[PDB]
Every structure is written in C-alpha cells, then in structure tokens.
Image 1 (tube, rainbow over the protein chains, first blue to last red):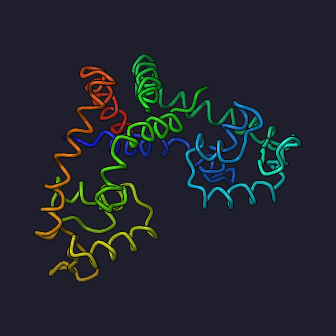
Image 2 (image 1 turned 45 degrees about the horizontal axis):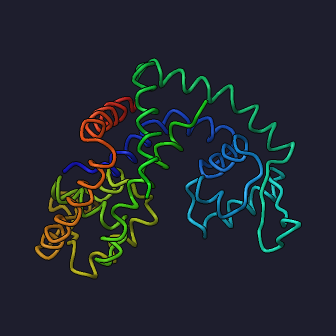
Length: 136
Length: 136
C-alpha cells in the first residue's frame, strides 16, 4: 500500500519549489503566506479556526500571528460579544502585500500548468476538493 | 486562484483523521510513522535523503531519529567508506512494529476507498505521482 498521505506531502514539495523563491524573494515563510491566503479569501477569522484551515499547529500559530501582527500584516481583536475569542484579519498593509505577491504567484501557477497540464491540474484540484469532503 | 498547495495539505488532514487514532492507539507520531514507512519500503537510507523523502525539516529529524533510536526502532551507522555520512535502517523490532500496525492501516485505507471511491483513489494517486515529477 503506497502512502496516500506521504504522497500528498511529496506532491506538495514538488509544487512548493515553484513558489518558495518568490516567498524567499519577498521575505515570507510559507506558513505566513497560508495565513495571508486564508485571511484574504475568507476574511476575518477566529484564531483556532484559522490554524485549522491554514494547517498550522497551535504552538507555531502563536508565533506566526505575533510576527505578522508585529509587521503590520494582521490585526487581532477580541470579539465584542465574547472576549475569550480572538479574531484575526489582514491590515491594509497585509492586503497590499497579498496584491503585490499575486502577479508572481500567478506566473508560478502558469509554470505549473504548462509543465503539469492544464486539465490535469483541474482534475487534481477537483479530486483533492472531493478528498477533503471525506473528513468524518 | 485556489491554492494547490494549501489544498494538498487540507486533503491530507482529511485522510489523516483515518490514521491518527491507530497511531494515537499505537503510541506513534505521524513523523515517526513516515520515517518507518520510508525505511520499510526503501531500506537503509542516508539521513538527509531520509528527511527529504519523509518530508521532515532537519532540526526535527534529529529528534525524530534519536527518539526512534532510543526506542529500538531504528539503528544509525557511519558509512564504512565515508564516515561523515550517516545511514539509517529499521531494526528487527522496528520491522515487527511496521508489521503489526499494517493490518490496522489497511482497514483505514479500506474505509477511505469506500468513502472516497476505489477508482477515484487510483486517479488521485496516479495524478499525485505525476505532480511529483514536475519537480525541477
């Protein structure tokens, strides 16, 4: 039995060589960029939920957020009607950060699409979207 | 542009809920189990190469190996004809560890196959095997 889950992770390392240089070049970690990506697409998010979607382990998430907060990328606030919840969102500076990286990240996806196949990329994503739906 | 790489990782979290309990139940971490899986399938392996295939970051790999070595699961040795290389292999105890977990891990794959689809699982794996081949 080949390992579905190890194979998912090796496939992701393969794709990540297309993005790490632009993130290298822009001075961000992939874990930062995941967080930025989710907060961009999904908007303000409760912080445990963000760790869960962004696929970060909770002890590293504390440092991920405090760093991004220190850099002016995200803002953290207590929910007015439950102060023990903490919501996170991109700042104007973080949104403009996302925007300037996006042209580079589109070109890296164009390189993946050419080298992998435009329809193969679409089947993979469809299938991966389906696999996520098997979660109990 | 949806994130191929974040989506790979969320799909993997989905599948991992099928295995973490048996690894919970057997007292292993997934990072240990990746290492055991690669050393089982591929045999003795140089230690940086093992980190690369097993998808572990080098500072965590040191602790992964020293723990597994302390538990009698792996053996580490210097290559006779290059003492600055360190090879790793499963011990008899680690091989029997792999064997006893494998029945549980097969059942968890049967659950995935039923809930995901037997042919969909095969297309996904074929496609992921292809994606790995795009690595520059």
